Structures are given as structure tokens and as C-alpha cells.
Length: 196
Ligand code: HEM
Ligand SMILES: [Cl-]
Ligand SMILES: [Cl-]
Ligand SMILES: [Cl-]
Ligand SMILES: [Zn+2]
Ligand SMILES: [Zn+2]
Image (tube, rainbow, N blue to C red; front, side):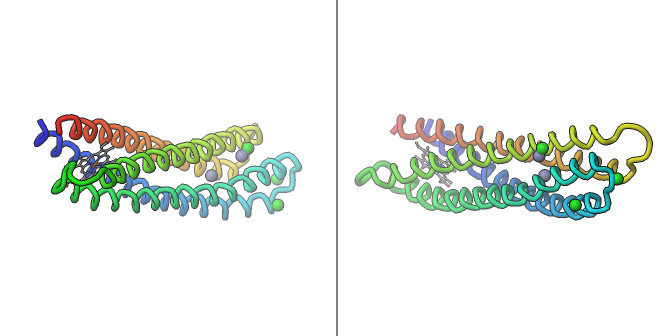
């Protein structure tokens, strides 16, 4: 009944708020690591004398720089979702008291905030998927230049890129969980209105 559904909706929102925090914190860890890996790449690229290696490392570096902008956009998208979550909280606490009374604008605002957060999480997801694909492409490029012996510095770059992919995967994993929570928030909140 409604008591149990209000409890579930409350619990889902608390979980969502924690997950959003963990996402943002991971983005900041991803920024740090990307910045650190770019330092190593720029040095390696500059020091490279083999044409093949130099050209590959320049393409990786070019695109890693672009990752910094994409990650900043991802973090701005997560912050916006946090701002909307605040508003869901305040409007939801008012809906707890008012219910369906008065005109529909409060109800609609809360539904519209939820729709907007779902759209932000889809954007965030897509931007993260774009970064992770390209990070994987840079693994494949590094492997092209890692034939034979030596390549010690290249192996260090590869190891860092592999740690990056681990983190990006975790980022997408949390985003998918967050999107699932938002679906459950929608379903439970719809049930709350249906039960009146
Ligand atoms: C991202 C999606 C959503 C989030 C984070 C969210 C969050 C919240 C929060 C924090 C509350 C106040 C809980 C409390 O009383 O302490 C609330 C209340 C409520 N929400 Fe949502 N909500 C979401 C989507 C929806 C949708 C789509 C609907 C309806 C279509 C809905 C209907 C309600 C209703 C009826 C209440 C009042 C009952 C209550 O306070 O427990 N919510 N929501
Ligand atoms: Cl260079
Ligand atoms: Cl070289
Ligand atoms: Cl590439
Ligand atoms: Zn990257
Ligand atoms: Zn690339």
C-alpha cells in the first residue's frame, strides 16, 4: 500500500543520491588519472624517434586531451543531476504533506524533474561510452607498436590505459545502476498517484 510504497520511494531516492555521489567522485578520480597519463604520453611522444611510434603516440595524446573536455562535460552533467535531485527532494517532501491537493503544477514539476534527470543520465552514459570506446582504441594502437622486445615505456603507458578502462567500466556500471533506480522511482511514484 501507499505506506510501503512511500518507504520504497524514499529508500530508492537515498540510494540514488549515494550512487550519484559515487559517480561524481569517480569522475574526479578519472580526471586525475587522465591528467597523469597525458603527462606520461606527452613525454613519450616527444622522446619518440621512430616515425610509426611517434605518429601513434601523437594520435593517442590528441584524443586523450579531448577526453579531458568530455570528462568535464560528464562532471557538469552529474552536477546538474544533483541540482535536480535537490529539487526532487524539496518538492517530494511538500508532496508528502499536500498530496494531490491544489492544482497539478507541483505534481507535474516533480514528474518533470524526474524526466529531466533521466535525460541527463542518458547523456552522461553516452559521453562515458564514447570515452571508453576510444580508450580501448588506444590500447589497440599501443599494441600495434609493442611487437618484439623493448617497449618498456610503451608498456607503462599500456598499463595505465588498462587501469583507466577499469575505471571507465565502473563509471558506466554505476550510471546504469543509477538509470535503473530512476526507473524504479518513476514506477513507484506512479503507483503512489494510482493508489491516491
Ligand atoms: C529521479 C526520480 C525521482 C526522485 C529522485 C524522487 C525523489 C523523491 C523524494 C526524495 C521524495 C520525498 C520522499 C520523502 O517523503 O522523504 C519524493 C516524494 C514523492 N515522489 Fe518522487 N522522485 C522521483 C520521481 C517521481 C515520479 C516520476 C513520481 C510520480 C510520477 C514521484 C512521485 C512522488 C510522490 C507522490 C511523492 C510523495 C510521497 C513521499 O514523500 O514519499 N516521484 N520523491
Ligand atoms: Cl610530439
Ligand atoms: Cl622511438
Ligand atoms: Cl583512436
Ligand atoms: Zn582517456
Ligand atoms: Zn582515439
